[PDB]
Image (cartoon, grey):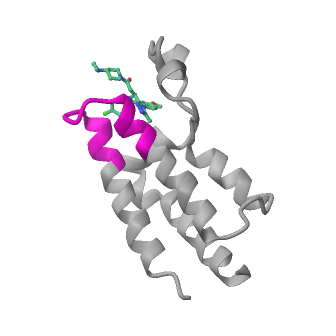
Amino acid sequence: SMEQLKHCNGILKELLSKKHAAYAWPFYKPVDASALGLHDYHDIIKHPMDLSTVKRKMENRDYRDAQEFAADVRLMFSNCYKYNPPDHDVVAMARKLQDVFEFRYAKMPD
Ligand SMILES: COc1ccc2c(c1)C(c1ccc(Cl)cc1)=N[C@@H](CC(=O)N1CCC(N(C)C)CC1)c1nnc(C)n1-2
């Protein structure tokens, strides 16, 4: 619905807000494989995703429903878990931001 997509825009605003910056910063823009020295990133990760891409899709009304929005946000986190070992600090940062996302997404009115 239009109303659920409105709640999703509020979730995205929360994920981009200053209170989460200490763990959100790796996710604001696409992974820059050249800058980071990740020569195999685009071989391993076939469908990159990040918050700037989710924001553009929300602004252009490209999500048909709330579930399509959730699939892109979960894809962003899944790519991080897929690429990195489980002991890495970026994985701990992803799980902190994901817990914000999953809590707010669960509270969406029907
Ligand atoms: C703008 O900076 C970014 C953007 C995307 C990143 C990363 C950093 C940060 C990053 C690293 C440390 C901290 Cl504390 C935070 C983030 N990691 C990269 C991954 C990275 O560089 N690795 C891969 C693992 C290697 N092991 C030695 C095995 C080291 C190099 C990354 N992956 N998903 C996202 C999103 N990312």
> Between 2 and 23, which is closer to the camera in this rendering?
2
Q: Is residue 83 above or below residue 58?
A: above
Q: Main secondary structure of the magenta part?
A: helix
> Between 17 and 46, which is closer to the camera in this rendering?
46
Kindly give the residue lying farthest to the right in the view shown.
60
Q: Is residue 107 above or below residue 56?
A: below
Image-based side of 70 in relation to 4, left or right: left
Position of residue 52 measured from the top left corner of the image (x, y, whole percent)? 63, 46
Q: Is residue 47 above or below residue 65?
A: above
Kindly give the residue lying farthest to the left in the view shown.
87
Kindly give the residue lying farthest to the bottom in the view shown.
110
If the picture is divided into quarters, which one holds ligand 1?
top left
At 22% from the left and 36% from the top, the residue drawn is: 86
Answer whether residue 93 is magenta in the image: yes
Image-based side of 46 in relation to 22, left or right: right
Answer whether residue 65 is magenta in the image: no
At 35% from the left and 39% from the top, the residue drawn is: 81
Q: Quadrant of the C terminus?
A: bottom right
Stretch of the chain drawn in magenta: 78-94
Position of residue 68 measured from the top left corner of the image (x, y, whole percent)? 62, 61
Q: Quadrant of the N terminus?
A: bottom right
> Between 57 and 66, which is closer to the camera in this rendering?
66
How many marks are shown on the rendered structure?
0
At 60% from the left and 77% from the top, the residue drawn is: 7
At 68% from the left and 83% from the top, the residue drawn is: 3
